[PDB]
Length: 123
Image (cartoon, rainbow, N blue to C red; front, top):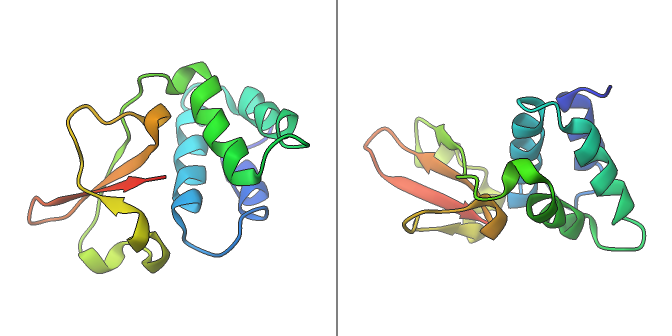
């Protein structure tokens, strides 16, 4: 079996840019998949509807819609020290967090500052 880190780097390589929301989503998919022994499934859903099939971003989103661990799953909260600790490329994807945010509905994660303020990352 493939490690979360390795599968992540494989995914990163298909992604335009750096530190985008889709990067953050890769990190979320690989973490949550690892917690569930689903990295196999995920790796294959990424390749199956990769070619062709969908764009890499679309293979990612399709993973959050098709792979069972993500259905009705709340986005993970990531605690950060400052508003600066959010990758610049994520800035144009940040939104206020609504009630009951869902990963399969596009919410990558929720950034929780020290002041208590939250910023949601949406794809």
